[PDB]
Amino acid sequence: GVVDILKGAAKDIAGHLASKVMNKL
């Protein structure tokens, strides 16, 4: 089922930036 996480990881990009800034906050 982890596979579903791979295809999602592609877009996780948008969230990756937030978490980046969010965490920094």
Image (cartoon, rainbow, N blue to C red):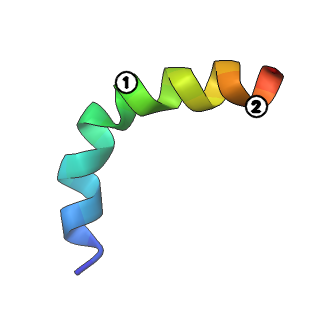
Going from N to C along the chain, the mark reached first, 2 or 1, is 1
What element does badge 1 sit on? helix
Amino acid bearing label 1: Ala
The circle drawn on residue 22 is none
Residue at position x 21%, y 68% from top?
3
- Look at mark 2 in the image and give the residue it sits on: 23
Residue 5 locus on image (x, y percent)? 29, 61
Q: Is residue 23 above or below residue 9?
A: above
Q: Whole-percent x and y of residue 18?
A: 54, 24
Residue at left offset 22%, top offset 81%: 1
Question: Which residue is at a point 19% across and 65% down the rendered structure image?
Answer: 4
Left or right of 1? Residue 9 is right
Q: Where is residue 19 in the image (x, y as percent from the top left)?
A: 60, 32
Q: Which quarter shows the C terminus? A: top right
Q: Which amino acid does label 2 sit on?
A: Asn
10 vs 12, left or right, is left
Q: In which quarter of the image is residue 20?
A: top right
- Residue at 24% from the left image edge and 48% from the top image edge: 8
**Which of 7 and 19 lies nearest the eye of the viewer?**
19
Coordinates of residue 14 in the picture (x, y in percent): 37, 24
Quadrant housing residue 15? top left
Which residue is nearer to you in this view: 18 or 2? 18
The residue that disc 1 covers is 14
For label 1, the crowd category at 10 Å Cα-Cα, with few meaning under 14, some 14 to 19 and many 20 or more, is few
Say how many tags the image has: 2
Q: What element carries label 2?
A: helix
